Structure formats: C-alpha cells, structure tokens
Image (cartoon, rainbow over all chains, first blue to last red; front, side, top):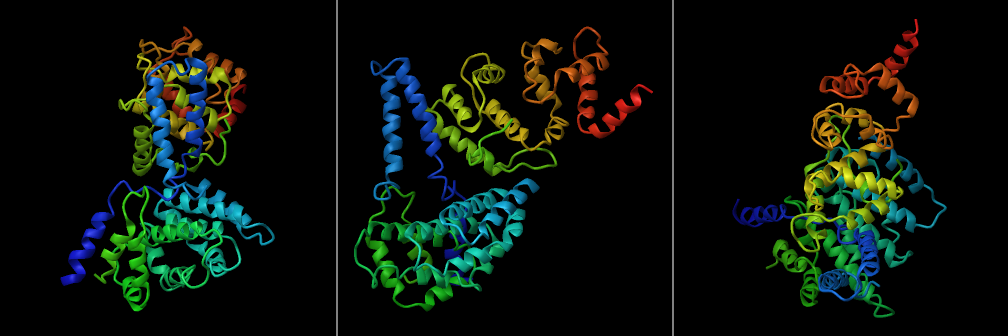
Length: 75
Length: 179
Length: 183
C-alpha cells in the first residue's frame, strides 16, 4: 500500500527476464575453444580467400568485444 | 536427484579439509552455487547446511587475495536468487552488514598498487547485492540505517559501465529510495 | 560412456521419475542454440557440435560417424532443435545408469530413431553397432536374438519391443529367470 507498493511490484516485473547466471558470461571458454577448433579446421579447409570466412571472422571479433567488456582489466 | 546430492557431499568433504590452498575450494563453492541453482528448491534445502563454512571464512577478508573474495561474491550471487529461506536466513546471520563491511575496501584504506581489481570488486559486489533484493520489507530498512553509503552510491553513479546488460547502480538507487 | 567432468553437461539436472530436463535448462539451451548459430538461420550445423562432443566426451571418429548419421534424420544435412535436445538427453542419461527407466516410456522415439529408413521394422544390421550406447555384449545379443524373435525373420515388432522395454527395468528377476530357464 502507498509508496511501499507501486515501486517494488515493478521490481518483481524485473524478476522475469532472460536472467543470465553470474557464470553464464564466463562458461563459454570451452565454447571459444571448440569454435577456435572450428576455425583451425576451417583454415585447413579453405583459408582466407572467401567471404563467409569474413562473416565468421566478424563473428570471432564480435565475441572478442563481447568477452572484452568483462576482460579488459581482469586479464 | 540423489547423484547431485552425493557428489556435492564428497566435494564438501574436500571443503572441510583445512590444510589446503583455498582457490580449488573456491571454484568448488562455485560448483555448489551453480548446481544448487540448477537443481531447484529441493537442492536449496539440501544445501541449507553448507553456509557454515563459507560464513566462517567470509570474515577473513583481510588475509587472502582479491580472487578469493570475488569468487565468493559470485558464489553467493549464484546461490542467493529465487531462494526464500536464504533471503530471510542471511539478514539475521551477518551477510548484508558484512557486504557493507566489504565495501570500505579502498576509499579510506588503500590508494593504488594495482587498483583496477578494486573496481572489479565493486562491480561484482553490486551485482551480488542487486540479486539479493527480492521483494521483502526487512533489508532496505537497515540499508536506510547507514549514512555515508548514499554518498558512495553517488560515486557508483559516476563511474562508467562498460558492456554490462544494464547499469545496476541506477536501478539500485531507484530501489534504495533515497531519491 | 565416460564424459569429461567439469563440463557444462555434467552440471545438468536429471530426474529419476520420468527421466527428463527442466524448462529453465532448455531455456538456457535455446539461448545457446540462438547464439551458436553463426549465420543465424534458426538451425544448427555439424562441425561445431562435432567439436563440442569432442570436448565433452572421449570418443573416436567412428562414434562421430554413427552419431552424426543417426542424428541426421532430417536428410538435408542441416540440423535443428529436437535432435539436439534428445541427443543431449540421451548422452546425459548414459552415466546415471537409469536409462532403462528412460526408454521405459520413450518407446516410440527410439523406434523412430532406429527406423532409419522408414519401414517400421528393424533389422540386426541397424543396432549391431549401437551397442556402445547400451553396453550389451555379443553373447546376450545372441540370447536376445534366439529368445525374443516372435517375428522369427531377424526382424522386430512394436509389441516385441514392448516386451523388450518391460524387460529392461527388472533385470534381477531376469537373472533368476535364466537361473530357472534350464530347469
């Protein structure tokens, strides 16, 4: 009731979302390992002469900036 | 069901070996946090015994390095959510005043040796304390009890948030009611 | 089958009543399915899951061989949701040693996966190399062949596998049954 009510109800509106766990932004290290294995099999496949090559290159820098935001200063 | 229970039983038996380095026990405590969250409610009242050891070691923050303290930050952050017996268990048993006690870290004690890890500690402790908020009435009264933290809350309004899902400090100040 | 400890698939929750997974875990897996598509076409390719099972298991390229043509039921090369979910269900149901309870009530799916060519009847050349999934040795292959062929023409049946799947959950009285059998 009153100023107790109208704020905190919206916070359980916050309580449904995708809600990543604290380790869901760091569990992908072996996912990077298996996709970099896909990169080295892909380098054994066709090399750099290609453009879906360029889109998976855009994917590897996209996840590079996606992991960089938690790993700028952590190193 | 019970295979998760028994495997955390023996790795908890590693957890009460005193004569070892703490870091493998810290990633073990990460495994309790993730496995207890992916179990559900029944895993949480199974794991209702196991905060004695981590509650014992969270008062020794002045001895170990920053890796150990940030590791039990996401251990309690992974454990705490959607957990009712937890969220009235912790404010009677020295947790959120201990997070306040964690927060003096470096604004009066140290200045710089390599002080980037200090704001990494603030990032992980604020992401720890947003996910313990739930919808109760008890905890923000004693959050209103302290005095200087709002000023420090102003400081976590000042610093930039790089690549986070959203800025947790401004929804924190929205939920803390000093606006 | 021994998977690698510390992997993500070792952290999942298995129930021992209907042998299934949770809604929130498959929500997490559709998030990983959404992010793992490089060309984002709501589907899945092969070599990523090949490297994924190389990380989480310890099986050589023949196992990649019959696994990757059992999962290719769609016969277009590009795979999707349901085969990924049921394959991760079965591979995390191996190590729990209660998989007999899992296909106790998953009869029609393992029919449809063992019907690799759509004639409703199953030959021995199909499952002669799928015994890594169920650790069944050749002597009890001979016993199951010469004791449970009502069809009698090295072929299978729906109600025959109903007897097979009520056979699978009660093996102690099955050893006492073969103790009685010669008498």
